[PDB]
Image: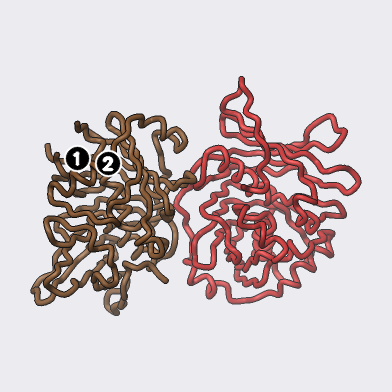
Chain colours: A brown, B red
Amino acid sequence: QGHPLVGTRSPVADEPDKYVWELTMDTDTFPWLEDHRVQGPIVFPGAGHLDLVVGCATEAFGPGRYSVENVEFRRPLFVFDDRPAPLVQVVLSPSMHFGVYSLQDGDKEWVLHSEGTVRAGAPDAEPPVPFAELEAHCPLEFDPAKVFAKFRNNGLMLGPTFRVISRLKYGELRSLGRIDTPDTIADEAPRHLIHPALLDACFQSLSIAMGNDKTLYIPFDVRRFSFHAKAGKRLYCYGQAHVIAYCEGDLWLFNEDGELVAEFEGFKGKS
Amino acid sequence: GHPLVGTRSPVADEPDKYVWELTMDTDTFPWLEDHRVQGPIVFPGAGHLDLVVGCATEAFGPGRYSVENVEFRRPLFVFDDRPAPLVQVVLSPSMHFGVYSLQDGDKEWVLHSEGTVRAGAPDAEPPVPFAELEAHCPLEFDPAKVFAKFRNNGLMLGPTFRVISRLKYGELRSLGRIDTPDTIADEAPRHLIHPALLDACFQSLSIAMGNDDKTLYIPFDVRRFSFHAKAGKRLYCYGQAHVIAYCEGDLWLFNEDGELVAEFEGFKGKS
């Protein structure tokens, strides 16, 4: 019944404020993994790491607001088809520094995928445009089928569960996207805080803020991710881009009733 | 919608002013019967916090709100001989609020509550984590003992305001379990924190000063009330008193899973 991405924890005696969760990230436990392939292999979406770490922190310290600051994404997490499911470790230090690690079977070394800090609580969120006014602030509309098309044309095989933007609007250095939970994940998504598929789609949405009539971007840095409330079945993602091959922007995720879900400050990306 | 937020009629020459109007009758709110003070029905001074924050929620949206420097001065009566009073939540552009009532045939409105309100809240600082709460308060008191004191001193409390199922205490400490009764179960999810349970929080705190006894205290001042999450069916209120006839304490409201619901800083009281 718990958060599906938080695994077993085995509190070690000589390390009292250290927390380690272990999880086998197989397709049987997570069929949706199939629908985010990058040039062939299945990749756990770099966005997904935020639902993972905060779900872990939630299990240790309790429900509420958590903030994940100075996240670095460096090495992709693969779920290959030829080898068995990888093992994944969320290591939280006493200093509240975290790392996400993976080991493929027969490998000598763990691979660090994500790195940052995490704390309880979050600043008061400051949307530059209130929820109701959002619709009008982004006049122009773009076809979601074209956005998905671009991704695959550059080698990003996105299946139904990662094709979840139903509507999308934009303006100068801004974007607004509607994220709908697909049926394939419906029963399982309320167990997550913000399902990785929907978290990935938020970064998809931001990519339309860079002025384009080409250059694919992937999560690289995040100054602050502040979780405020669980995602519902329908989501409104409002992005504002900042002005090389590094895209940057700030993000505000809302539920349809207008409840802020999460705030991203400094969501940097890379080709 | 929130049952205590009424009609709002935005006035043209006053754009940042909000006024909600409500007839506080027993038919709309049967639970009102169960908090009488020396005869007449009194809207609990604690209830003013669910009212103002429900109003602010309606204007600005769901999320965290903080009500600072609340003064309670004059009781809000729902007499039996006269028709239901009218109640007005006036929110100024400066985010200063007042709660007013007019009884039938009266020339002037009566100010009941006064303070400010803003969006957001500080990160909450429980001095004892939720899990450790149980052990921090060893000694137990009989709730039928506390309701008895109130009645003996002229506070006729009916079933809906007898909601403390369990109560534990220590030096300058208290811990109470607040249960939503069946009579309002159907209506409580519409409130943020039903007034009955909000009143019971102050009931709980009164056991932190008291030493095993006849001095009733009633809400008077609150430096800060910070709302974080809707109340559930079971609630744990942890109070810590501060050391004339003005009691004061800090309160931390928790749900069963340990989700902080509300923080009270500087909850002063008066005989």
- Which comes sooner in the sequence, label 1 or label 2? 2
Residue B172 seen from this side: no
Residue B210 image position (x, y, % from top left): 69, 65
- Write down the residue under mark 1: A247
**Callout 2: few (<14), some (14-19), or many (20+) C-alpha neighbours within 10 Å?**
many
Left/right placement of residue A212 relative to residue A194 reads left
Task: Identify the residue at horizontal 15%, vertical 56% (top origin).
Answer: A38
Residue A32 image position (x, y, % from top left): 28, 63
Residue B178 seen from this side: yes
Whether tag 1 and tag 2 are in contact, CB under 8 A, the answer is: yes
Task: Identify the residue at horizontal 87%, vertical 33% (top origin).
Answer: B105
The amino acid on which the numbered mark 2 sits, given as a three-letter code, is Leu
User: Alpha-carbon distance for marks 1 and 2?
Assistant: 9 Å
Task: Identify the residue at horizontal 14%, vertical 72% (top origin).
Answer: A104
Q: Secondary structure at mark 1?
A: loop
Left/right placement of residue A100 relative to residue B116 reads left
| Residue A29 found in image quarter | bottom left
The lab-note entry on whether marks 1 and 2 share a chain reads yes
Left/right placement of residue A263 relative to residue B23 reads left
